[PDB]
Length: 401
Figure 1 (cartoon, rainbow, N blue to C red):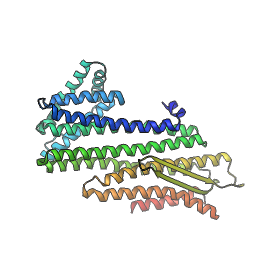
Figure 2 (cartoon, rainbow, N blue to C red):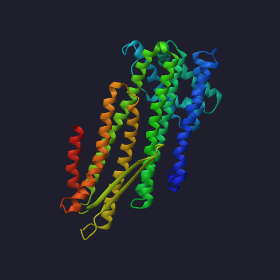
Figure 3 (cartoon, rainbow, N blue to C red):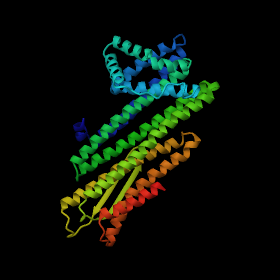
Figure 4 (cartoon, rainbow, N blue to C red):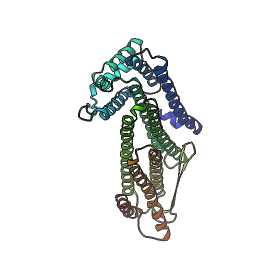
C-alpha cells in the first residue's frame, strides 16, 4: 500500500527491491529447469502436452507473484514472438498481421485465468483455451510445431511478461513514492521518498536489462542446440532485439519530452523574485546496480522580496525536477549501455545516438539551473524563468543537431 510505504524503513525498502530481484531470478531458474526437463526427460510427450505443463507453471507463478492481466500480456508476447519467426520464414505478407487485442478477448483470457487459479478444472479450461486458440495454432503450424523452437519462444514470452508485470509494480511503487514526497514536501521525509523514487528507477533499469540478457541467452542456447538453423535464428533474434530497442528509444523520446514539459511548467509557476546561489546533482551507481541521486539546491538569502514560502516552494520544485529527471535519464542510460552489447551491428550507432541524447538531456537540464545560479550569484538581474527559457531553447537546438 501507499501507507505501507509511508511507514516503511530504509532497510525494509532495500529488502523489498532486492526481494523483487531474487523472486525474478528464481522464477527464471525454475522455468529453465522445467524447459530442459520437458525437452530431455519427457521425449514421449507431444508439443501440446509440453505446452500444457508450461501453462500450468505460468498460472502458478503469476497468480502467486503478479496479477491476472499478465495472462493477456503473455498471450500478446507469445503471439508476437511466433509471428516474428513465421515472418522470417515465410515473409510478412503470408504471416498474420501484428495482433489487435480486442476488449472481449482480453476479458475472456483474464476470466479464464482467474478460474484457473481456483480449481483444476479451471486450469484445464484455461489451457484448452490457449492451446485451441485458432490464431496461435496457425503460427505454430507455420513453425512446423518444432518443440525446441516453440518452447524457447514460450520461455522468452514468459520472461518478457514477468518483467512487464515487475515494471508495472515498480511504476506503482515510484508513483506512490512521489505522492508521499509531495505530501512531505520541503522536509527530509520528502527527500527520503524522492530517494525511494530514484531507487525504483534503478530497479526498472535492472529489469529491462534482465529481459535483454535472458533473451540473448535463450537465443544463444537455441543456436547451440539447432546449428542448422543458425541463419534463421540469427535473423529472428535481430528482429526481437530490434523491437526491444525501439521500445527503449520510444521511452527515451517520451522521458525527454516529459522532463522538458516539467521544466516549462516549473518555470511558469516560479515567483520571479526567487534566485539561486548554487545547484549540485550527484548520480551514484553501486557495482550491483543500485541508484542514488542526491540534489542540493541553494536559494539566495537577503531582503529580495520573496516570501520564505515561495522560496521553499521553488527550491522543492527544482529539487524534485532534478531528482526525478536525473533518476529517469540515468536509468535509461544504463539500459542503453547494456543494449549496446546486444543489438545487431547496424543498430549500435543508433544506441550511441540515444546515449548521447540522454547524456545531453541530463547534463543540459542540470546545467540550466547551475548556470542560472552562477549568473545570479555573479550579480545578473535576470530571472530564473528567463535564463531557463533561453537555455532550454539552446538545449533543444543541440538535441536537434
